[PDB]
Image: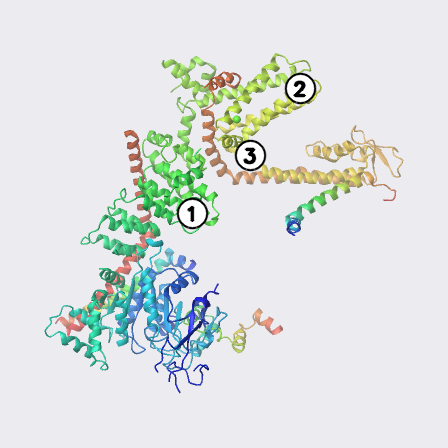
């Protein structure tokens, strides 16, 4: 996408030649037919640019170095937009324009060290921009080599080149109005002249300013200054939240023209940093500022003396230099001197103080947040001399939140930053407004002032600053921010489970894919953290408090912790011992969890025994209801009722089922089945009508019960009709099978059998594989045998029998040799067809079979027996063994999870058994400070757990090794210092 | 390698395209990956570097009787 | 990413610490020699 | 025409070709079995 690039940007060709030789820098001969003082704009013609695209320096580089040619009189907004958007460069956190003449190809060692170590390092750390001449000469070359050395030794800095068109060596190769996306640049040009220079190969971007001249210097000064000012007017990301981008000018040596440029920059309110001892045109200003409030007598001509000394003799006589120095001092607040300090190389702090002084609201904390320098912020805060205001830190906190800098927010909060007063509906709206472009949260907010209530309602279903901040972070999916807020939350466990729920639902709702997977991962991390916190809260402290923690219903959604876990499928959460013990206790209701099963049975059959001490736990009726109200006793009663129901069903079906009108027992059976139907109706109805109906029908067991009951009704209806008695009997016969299959549910309660049942459920893929394999083989062998025999019955039912049924039973040791092996049969001439025939003795083995090639029949029999009885069955064994070995853990977790659903289901069933449950359905028809202390105790445990994790991490070997590396680096730094002092003392010895 | 990196990093020393081209050829022939990496990283023009003569030289460095050598001979 | 991960591995960090300690010992020998020279020049 | 384009897309998809081929193969086996077990006679085919 570049079609607009020629549109908004224009190159400059001079309209008029002004003297043989033009002022335009081109020979008189090479000029257009249109050819007192030449003007760079008045006598210039504009046309669409023809030298855009990107460079590919021959050899090294990132294979991408964007280049542009534009007129000097170009608005900077378009340039900034181009760089930020089209070329993909991130907005700058700081712009350092490195002025400087640097006379001579070689620069002093201390200056080169300062550049390479401070300037480039700080630029990389803070993601700043370096603006210099994009030429392999002057200060630009030094900057480029410094950047290259830093990149090599670091184990990518962004620097641009603003250079005049006409002085770029080999400009022709870059000319391509269509486009020069690839671009070969011969920067190793053998000829060397000062009229033109090659482009440095270390600069990521270029700005070949043009002013209709074939060579000159300084033409780009206007554009450079305007660009710097415009960048200074922008903001540091996060919409308008970002502070004004700091822009700083660094000056080393230079000339009078550099003094003029410094004056222009100061006029444009741009801070300037001067290096002491750099050389001419730079150290003079440093000295003058050092003079500052010098005495009027004997100082007025001191400035002139300094000008004539530091500056070159030319123009020294001219008073213009002194007047310009005075004008510069007029705004000395924007000037600073780089204290040499024997090569301090502490660039960032000097820049910070210079920016603060220039500002005279921009604050150190806001700048530190704008950059990623946590150390700067902590140093500034730790400085006791500096005093901070509530809003002073509030602005910084807002910036940190908007830009997602967890470390900064942590540090700011830790420094006594009031939070309750900090958050406001306006600020919260701002925070939510920072949704990244088209994110799912943004779509949800648009579809829905934050107005976050409705989005949460539509997410969950709906069927304290920390809480709000945590919710916002979860919505925006800022992992570290959310984790930190949770660490400061109040309802830690319930908060964690709610976060897991919300993240999982959002992820299933995201078009994010791998980004959604990170939300899924964040959900897993939160679930694990909640698990660990609860495990600590339970084992290490009173279990009663843990029980209270789970049962309570916080304000997250007015739902219990267990409900949240179940809705989020937080399988890991239920897997821990504490939750299982609590669930067991609820399962036994009021009676003790240790009650032996046999004791329970004896109590069940001997109601009076419940009052004996042999079972552990008006008082009498209260105890009675407790016993009969416990979920376990309801379960046992229901099982007994179900068994009696099956017994009655079997009795009726096998004996009393007659064509006559139904008897007493059959009617009792009908009433019983109707009771079961009412029970399932109750379960479905109360367990949003469509939503709960789907929830009920989802459970497989309920599907089984429903199919059983519908088949039962179908069969009864059929039997009542006079004609369909047999059909009714048959349907009821199958319905008995369907009912009795339900008894498998009894093994979902045991501590060992439930996992076995789940694993069996997962074996069905292997079962189907074997079934289809056997089906194919059966079809093959059966058809082959039947074809070879050629029985004369040729009756479709008989054909199907001999093709499938008999081969099938051959798998299970029913091998009728007398019906296939001719040797066991009497030879007879049954059929008129030519050949021989025999007479099988079997009733359904065919009237008579051929015997043409019977040895082949026996051979096929042997092959089939082998493949079926041995190979297929053993393959199935192996597949079962492998699958069972592979899915043990997942099955166990799944059972532990569903244990809660089971318990809840049985916790609300009517107290009575199905056969009498009609009476209970009828009844159903016709119809603090302690909490605060609990939360405080939970928060204390959370703090202990967090400290334990942090300390354990800090004591790990890897962290200790890293810290030792840091200390060794510090030791080497100090060793260099003492070595330098040693050299100084050795010198002073003489 | 350290000697080469020190020599290159020395700003006083100026290098020529062929000046590094000879070194690059030597590094390739002797199979010194670090040297070639460093040389290329130092703004060494590559498109102009390779030539059919140079490529023939490179392929001529097949070690004694190697399968590549047999295949080239057969071709 | 691969290069940085390798450089941040424990083994590489330990090797780099060994290099830095060797450099420290070199400089320590230098300063010790200068210490002896200064002690001599004291008289 | 959009209609024919959609039609060809459906019937051109590899999966649909696979399903069609499977159905054809099953019918072929069924025909084979029928012929072999019933209509296979010494008389001309
Ligand atoms: Ca049910």
Image quadrant occupied by the C terminus of chain A: bottom left
Is residue A78 positioned above or below A483 on the image? Answer: below
Which numbered dot is residue C24?
Answer: none
**Is disc 2's CB within 8 Å of ligand 1?**
no
Mark before the other along the chain sequence, 1 or 3: 1
Crowding around mark 1 (Cα neighbors within 10 Å: few <14, some 14 to 19, many 20+) is some
Give the chain of mark 2. A
Name the front one of labels 3 and 2: 2
Q: Which residue is mark 1?
A: A442
Quadrant housing residue A538 = top left
Residue at image point 29% right, 69% down = A113
A272 or A938, nearer to the observer: A272
Quadrant housing residue A849 = top right
A30 or A405, nearer to the observer: A30
Is residue A189 positioned above or below D39 on the image? Answer: below
Q: Which residue is mark 2?
A: A719
Q: Which residue is mark 3?
A: A760
Give the chain of mark 3. A
Name the front one of labels 1 and 2: 1
Give the chain of mark 1. A
Q: Same chain for the residues at labels 1 and 2, yes or no? A: yes
How far is disc 3 from disc 2 in space, using C-alphas?
36 Å
């Amino acid at each position: 996408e570049q079609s607009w690039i020629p549109k908004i940007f224009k190159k400059k060709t001079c309209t008029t030649f002004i003297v043989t030789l033009c002022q335009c820098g081109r020979p008189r001969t090479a000029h257009p037919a249109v050819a007192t003082v030449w003007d760079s704009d008045a006598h210039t013609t504009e046309k669409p640019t023809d030298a855009y695209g990107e460079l590919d320096f021959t050899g090294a580089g990132r294979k991408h170095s964007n280049f542009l040619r534009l007129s000097d009189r170009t608005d900077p907004a378009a340039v900034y937009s181009l760089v930020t958007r089209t070329w993909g460069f991130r907005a700058p956190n700081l712009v350092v324009s490195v002025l400087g003449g640097s006379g001579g190809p070689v620069l002093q060692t201390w200056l080169q060290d300062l550049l390479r170590r401070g300037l480039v390092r700080a630029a990389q750390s803070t993601g700043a921009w370096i603006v210099t001449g994009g030429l392999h000469t002057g200060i630009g070359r030094h900057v480029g080599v410094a950047v290259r050395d830093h990149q090599m030794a670091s184990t990518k800095v962004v620097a641009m080149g603003v250079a005049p068109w006409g002085v770029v060596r080999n400009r022709d190769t870059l000319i391509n109005p269509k486009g020069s996306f690839p671009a070969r640049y011969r920067w190793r040009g053998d000829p060397e002249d000062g009229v033109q220079f090659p482009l440095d190969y270390n600069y990521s971007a270029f700005f070949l300013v043009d002013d209709g001249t074939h060579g000159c210097l300084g033409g780009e000064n206007r554009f450079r200054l305007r660009l710097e000012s415009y960048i200074s007017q922008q903001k540091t990301g996060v919409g308008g939240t970002g502070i004004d981008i700091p822009v700083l000018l660094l000056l080393i040596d230079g000339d009078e023209k550099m003094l003029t440029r410094i004056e222009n920059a100061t006029q444009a309110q741009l801070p300037c940093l001067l290096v002491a001892g750099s050389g001419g045109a730079a150290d003079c200003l440093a000295e003058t500022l050092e003079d500052t409030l010098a005495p009027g007598s004997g100082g007025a001509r001191q400035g002139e003396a300094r000008d004539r000394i530091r500056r070159f003799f030319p123009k020294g006589d001219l008073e213009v230099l002194q007047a310009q120095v005075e004008r510069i001092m007029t705004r000395k607040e924007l000037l600073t001197v780089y204290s040499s300090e024997d090569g301090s190389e502490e660039f960032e702090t000097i820049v910070l103080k210079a920016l603060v002084k220039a500002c005279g609201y921009l604050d150190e904390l806001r700048l530190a947040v704008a950059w990623n320098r946590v150390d700067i912020a902590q140093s500034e805060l730790f400085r006791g001399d500096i005093q901070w205001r509530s809003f002073h830190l509030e602005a910084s906190l807002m910036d940190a939140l908007l830009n997602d800098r967890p470390e900064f927010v942590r540090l700011l909060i830790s420094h006594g930053l009031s939070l309750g007063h900090f958050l406001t509906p306006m600020r919260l709206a701002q925070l939510y407004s920072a949704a990244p472009s088209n994110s799912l949260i943004r779509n949800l907010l648009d579809q829905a002032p934050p107005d976050v209530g409705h989005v949460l309602r539509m997410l969950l279903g709906k069927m304290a600053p920390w809480s709000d901040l945590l919710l916002w972070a979860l919505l925006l999916n800022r992992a570290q921010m959310a984790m930190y807020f949770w660490e400061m939350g109040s309802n830690a466990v319930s908060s964690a489970l709610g976060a897991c729920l919300l993240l999982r639902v959002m992820a299933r709702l995201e078009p994010d894919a791998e980004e959604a997977a990170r939300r899924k991962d964040l959900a897993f991390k939160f679930e694990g953290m909640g698990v660990d916190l609860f495990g600590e809260c339970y084992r290490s402290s009173e279990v009663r408090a843990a029980r209270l923690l789970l049962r309570r219903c916080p304000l997250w959604g007015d739902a219990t912790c267990l409900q949240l876990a179940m809705q989020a499928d937080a399988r890991a959460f239920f897997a821990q011992d504490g939750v299982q013990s609590l669930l067991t206790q609820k399962w036994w209701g009021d009676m003790a969890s240790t009650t032996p099963i046999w004791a329970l049975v004896l109590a069940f059959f001997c109601p009076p025994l419940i009052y004996t001490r042999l079972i552990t736990f008006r008082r009498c009726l209260r105890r009675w209801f407790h016993f009969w109200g416990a979920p376990v006793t309801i379960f046992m009663g229901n099982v007994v009722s179900y068994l009696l129901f099956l017994l009655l069903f079997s009795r009726v079906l096998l004996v009393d089922f007659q064509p006559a009108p139904p008897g007493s027992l059959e009617l009792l059976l009908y009433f019983w089945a109707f009771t079961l139907l009412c029970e399932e109706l109750r379960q479905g109805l109360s367990g949003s009508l469509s939503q709960r109906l789907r929830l009920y029908l989802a459970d497989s067991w309920n599907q089984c019960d429903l199919v059983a009951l519908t088949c039962f009704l179908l069969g009864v209806g059929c039997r009542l009709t006079p004609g369909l008695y047999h059909l009714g009997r048959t349907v009821l016969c199958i319905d008995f099978m369907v009912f009795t299959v339900r008894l498998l549910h009894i093994f979902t309660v045991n501590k060992q059998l439930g996992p076995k049942i789940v694993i069996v459920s997962k074996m069905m893929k292997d079962v189907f594989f074997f079934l289809f394999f056997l089906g194919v083989w059966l079809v093959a062998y059966g058809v082959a045998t039947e074809g070879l025999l050629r029985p004369r019955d040729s009756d479709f039912p008989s054909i199907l029998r001999r093709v499938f049924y008999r081969p099938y039973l051959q798998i299970f040791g029913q091998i009728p040799q007398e019906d296939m092996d001719v040797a066991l049969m009497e030879h007879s001439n049954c059929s008129s067809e030519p050949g021989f025939w025999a007479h099988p003795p079997g009733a359904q083995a065919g009237t008579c079979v051929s015997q043409y090639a019977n040895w082949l029949v026996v051979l096929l029999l042997v092959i089939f027996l082998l493949v079926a009885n041995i190979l297929l069955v053993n393959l199935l064994i192996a597949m079962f063994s492998y699958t069972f070995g592979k899915v043990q853990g997942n099955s166990d977790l799944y059972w532990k999870a569903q244990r809660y659903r089971l318990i809840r289901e049985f916790h609300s069933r009517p107290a009575l058994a199905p056969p009498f449950i009609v009476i209970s359905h009828l009844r159903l028809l016709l119809r603090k400070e302690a909490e605060r202390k609990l939360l405080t105790w939970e928060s204390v445990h959370k703090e202990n757990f967090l400290l334990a994790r942090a300390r354990d991490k800090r004591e790990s070997d890897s962290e200790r090794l890293k810290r030792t590396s840091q200390k060794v680096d510090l030791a080497l730094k100090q060793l260099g210092h003492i070595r330098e002092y040693e050299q100084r003392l050795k010198v002073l010895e003489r």
